[PDB]
Image: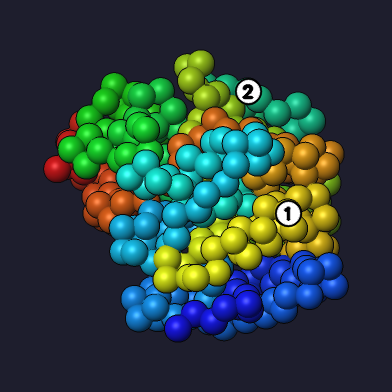
């Protein structure tokens, strides 16, 4: 029921979907094949319910973690890219769209949390987390705070705790091991003890979250924060002379943020394989396609190497790609959901002190 000789794409409206229209019309003037894009709400609700019937879009731009599950569900098509085009992109982006050894989608955008700092309050950023307590002693002498971020999510805290030995699921050869949920490790212990040392001596607060953190950083009260791309423009409302860099390393092991990769999955019911593959390889994942989509809304760190060299003049993009290449790729498995139910309670037992470090982490283990 997916139509032939014709391409329809669904893409969320927080992106440069008009840029997707622009690359569609380049494809139309060059080859004569019409490309339509549509941007309604709830597209992640909308794709699988229609793809289980065999219809809907041909291409979908979304995060990779629900793609691997839809790689199980028979809704994403097994792509066949060449090896030279696999060299054209970064392979750590290709590890985002792996499931059962098969390759399901072309990565476009890559997301990773980076350190955002006021250049005025601190002209020289530190490279160790062990430096953060001491310098905090300086900022209380100016009525300032060192670091303030969202402690209510494991998505923020996982770079530090999992830097020196923690890892969500064991992931090798494109397969996530279900029996190998790593939180009962000495590295996770060290990271959570460093968290309780930052909270016990009152360097930060435990009831803080994202709103107070970002609002105080826009005022310039807290000097350091950790954030992805989505708040960058918000800091550009503050007009604070700020910079973006990599997160500090900890005990030599660098931080490990969640790498969120926006990829374009081809529907598995599609008889339009080669057309969409041509549109993705020769038009999308090239310099001019990512340029045309970034003129409306950027993609931060992208997967294509040459376009990463074009965008690496922006230091935010360089910080994003280095945190992405040293980070942990997001799991494509549904047990991750229980992860977001388990380990979150761990920090609710940690920063609140209802349990200790080991008690909270082994409660999140099972």
Comparing labels 1 and 2, the label whose residue is closer to the camera: 1
Picture residue at 81% right of the left edge, 62% below the top = 292
Q: Is residue 294 visible?
A: no
Q: Is residue 8 above or below residue 356?
A: below
Instruction: First in sequence, mark 1 or 2: give its number.
Output: 2
Mark 2 crowd level (few <14, some 14–19, many ≥20, 10 Å Cα): some
Picture residue at 27% right of the left edge, 33% below the top = 182
Picture residue at 25% right of the left edge, 38% below the top = 177
Q: Is residue 16 above or below residue 290?
A: below
Reading the image, the residue beneath label 2 is 127
Mark 1 crowd level (few <14, some 14–19, many ≥20, 10 Å Cα): some
Label ID, residue 282? 1
Q: Position of residue 160 (x, y in %)?
A: 45, 33
Task: Classify the position of the C terminus by image quarter.
Answer: top left
Instruction: State which quadrant residue 19 falls in.
Output: bottom right
Picture residue at 32% right of the left edge, 39% below the top = 175
Q: Position of residue 131 (x, y in %)?
A: 57, 22
Q: Is residue 96 above or below residue 212?
A: above
**Count of numbered tags:** 2
Q: Residue furthest top?
A: 252
Q: Is residue 24 above or below residue 113?
A: below
Q: Position of residue 32 (x, y in %)?
A: 78, 75
For this view, does 183 lie left or right of residue 164? left
Which secondary structure lies at badge 2? loop
Which secondary structure lies at badge 1? helix
Q: Nearer the viewer, residue 279 or 227?
A: 279
Q: Position of residue 84 (x, y in %)?
A: 66, 36
Q: Nearer the viewer, residue 129 or 283?
A: 283
């Amino acid at each position: 029921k997916i139509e032939e000789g014709k391409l329809v794409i669904w893409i969320n409206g927080d992106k440069g979907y008009n840029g997707l229209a622009e690359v569609g019309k380049k494809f139309e003037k060059d080859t004569g094949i019409k490309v339509t894009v549509e941007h309604p709400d709830k597209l992640e609700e909308k794709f699988p319910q229609v793809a289980a019937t065999g219809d809907g879009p041909d291409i979908i731009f979304w995060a990779h973690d629900r793609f691997g599950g839809y790689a199980q569900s028979g809704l994403l098509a097994e792509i066949t890219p060449d090896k030279a085009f696999q060299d054209k992109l970064y392979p750590f982006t290709w590890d985002a769209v792996r499931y059962n050894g098969k390759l399901i989608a072309y990565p476009i955008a890559v997301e990773a949390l980076s350190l955002i700092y006021n250049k005025d309050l601190l002209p020289n950023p530190p490279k160790t987390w062990e430096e953060i307590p001491a310098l905090d002693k300086e900022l209380k002498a100016k009525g300032k705070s060192a670091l303030m971020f969202n402690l209510q999510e494991p998505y923020f805290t996982w770079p530090l705790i999992a830097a020196d030995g923690g890892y969500a699921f064991k992931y090798e050869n494109g397969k996530y091991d279900i029996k190998d949920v790593g939180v009962d490790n000495a590295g996770a212990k060290a990271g959570l003890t460093f968290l309780v040392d930052l909270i016990k001596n009152k360097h930060m607060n435990a009831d803080t979250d994202y709103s107070i953190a970002e609002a105080a950083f826009n005022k310039g009260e807290t000097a350091m924060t950790i954030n992805g791309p989505w708040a960058w423009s918000n800091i550009d409302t503050s007009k604070v002379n700020y910079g973006v860099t990599v997160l500090p390393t900890f005990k030599g092991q660098p931080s490990k943020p969640f790498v969120g990769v926006l990829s374009a999955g081809i529907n598995a019911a599609s008889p339009n394989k080669e057309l969409a593959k041509e549109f993705l390889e020769n038009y999308l994942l090239t310099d001019e396609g990512l340029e045309a989509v970034n003129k409306d809304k950027p993609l931060g760190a992208v997967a294509l190497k040459s376009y990463e060299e074009e965008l690496a003049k922006d230091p935010r993009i360089a910080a994003t790609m280095e945190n992405a290449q040293k980070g942990e790729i997001m799991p494509n498995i549904p047990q991750m959901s229980a992860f977001w139910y388990a380990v979150r309670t761990a920090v609710i037992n940690a920063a609140s002190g209802r349990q200790t470090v080991d008690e909270a982490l082994k409660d999140a283990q099972t």
